[PDB]
Structure formats: C-alpha cells, structure tokens
Image (cartoon, coloured by chain):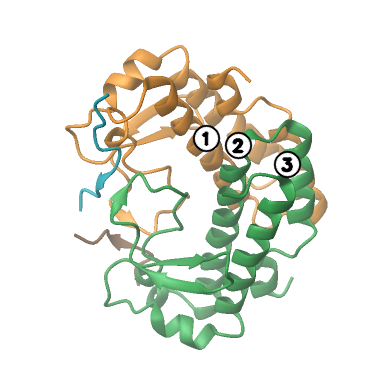
Chain colours: A green, B orange, C brown, D cyan
Amino acid sequence: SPRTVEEIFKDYSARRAALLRALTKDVDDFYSQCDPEKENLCLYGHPNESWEVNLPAEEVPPELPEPALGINFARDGMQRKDWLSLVAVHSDCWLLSVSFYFGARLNRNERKRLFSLINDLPTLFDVVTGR
Amino acid sequence: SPRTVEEIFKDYSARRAALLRALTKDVDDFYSQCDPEKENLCLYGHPNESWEVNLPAEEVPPELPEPALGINFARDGMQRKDWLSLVAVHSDCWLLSVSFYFGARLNRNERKRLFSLINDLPTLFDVVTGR
Amino acid sequence: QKKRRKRST
Amino acid sequence: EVRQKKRRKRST
C-alpha cells in the first residue's frame, strides 16, 4: 500500500487519470455501462489507470473506502451534464478519501503537503462542468 | 446545504465532535451498538454533534457520501483497539468526503483554506491511537 | 424522474 | 489464537 506522500500522490494521480478518462474521452462508453436496469453500480479508478463500472464489494467492510453506490440509478433522472457532475463530485470525494485512508499515519505537515499536490490539479467536477 | 468555507467547516466540526464522542466518551456504548448479529451498520456523525449507529441509506445514490458499511462485521474479528482505529480512519475519511462534497464549487484557494482548517484539528485516528 | 432508488438485493 | 471473520457479505 502507498505510504509516503509521493507514493500516495502517484496512486491518486493514476486513479484520477482513469476517472477523468471515464468522464471525458470515454464518456459514451461509461454512460452506456451505467445502465439503469442493472443492479447498483459504482465507478472505480485503479492505480494502473484503468476505470471500472461494477457492483460494490461483496464483503464489507471493504479494505478501501468505496465509491458512491448506484450511480446508474440516477442516470436517466436528470440531464446528462448534471449526472456527469454528480458522478464527478462523488469521484473527487472518493479520490480524497482513498488518499487520506492510505495517509492516515502521515503527520499534519505531510497531510498538508499531500493535499497541496492534489489541489494543484483541476477537480473532476471542475473539468466536467467547464470551470 | 453548507456552501461557504465557514459553513462547511462548521458542519465538519460538529460531525467530528459527534464521532470523537462516539470513539472516546461513549466508546463502550458505541462498541455495544455495533452488534455483529445485526445487519450491516455504519457510524454517522450529524451536524447537531450527535452520533448514530444505523443501517445505510435505503435509496441510492445517497444525497451525501456514506460512511463505511458493516463495521459491526469487523468488530469481533479484531482486537478492540485495532477495530477502533479502523473505524477512526474510515470516519476521518468520511468527514473529509462530506466536506468536499459540500465544497464542490469552492475555488482552489478556498479548498486549500478548508483543508487547512480540517488539518489543524487532531484526526480521529490520532486521538484514538494516541499519536 | 427519480434521483435514487432502493439499493439492490 | 482464534480468528473470527472480519468481513461478511453485505446484508442485501
């Protein structure tokens, strides 16, 4: 598991790259994957920069914090731009949660430094909404 | 919902006060409420500074990020101090996720400020583990 | 329509 | 020592 600020930010950046791709370059494919008629789905970003739409972890509590559940249940109930922004904010939050789960043993100043690396990047919400 | 940095951090601080209380002053009762025989349970901190152990949101995706699910399924399989530290880190991550959910529309400087306010308070993990 | 619905069984 | 399960299938 990532431990240092640098290891955690490398992991963060790879998962974020995956989620950004799902929400922009691959958006039609991602949208189709989030079928409202499937069971409840989550969007994951993995440290090999792959994204994944799937059921949540079968066994709980999971090893890592979980992404928002059932995003496919919201897809057809709002405009596409609003659904993508909803997925984006929850994904931003998941990225932060995973990073500071790994970073639980960092001291105050190292946690601050980790956030400064994260905060130099546009959020997924920023990108998808065109801020 | 909270929207300014001040409003979001007031909300954070109250939810944190609730979860700190669950993990310290009220820890015996909190531990006993995480009944392994019950369905999957979560620890919530509310903006009126009260804590609650309950089932997750019935309808998904929930309005707010959700706390870690099924912490009662982990209680008897670990030593108490290790279970409490696990709940603590997941609770720290949930507090951060909730605040930056509300803070989706904050700018880069405001996000930095919000994290600096959060980061200056001892984490639940550090309180529980004595770090 | 709906923003959410019950979690899957 | 005895090691009970630490995870279980989600209640749904």
Tell which of A5 and A73 is nearer to you. Answer: A5
Please give the label number shown on residue B114. Answer: 3
Q: What is the spatial separation of the Cα atoms under label 2 and label 3, in whole angstroms?
A: 18 Å
Does dot 2 land on a helix, a strand or a loop?
Answer: helix
Which residue in the protein does label 1 denote?
A: B89
Q: Can residue B107 be seen in this view?
A: no
Q: Which chain carries label 1?
A: B
Q: What residue type is labelled 3?
A: Leu
Q: Which amino acid does label 2 sit on?
A: Ala
Q: Name the residue under label 2.
A: A104
Chain ID at mark 3:
B
Describe residue B55's horizontal placement relative to residue A24 as left or right.
left
Q: Left of A107 or right of it: where is A45?
A: left
Q: Nearer the viewer, residue A104 or C5?
A: A104
Q: In which quarter of the image is residue A103?
A: top right
What residue sits 56% from the left and 47% below the top?
A: B97
Q: Give coordinates of residue B130: x percent, y percent.
A: 59, 17
Residue at 55 percent across and 21 percent down: it is B129
- Mark 1 secondary-structure assignment: helix
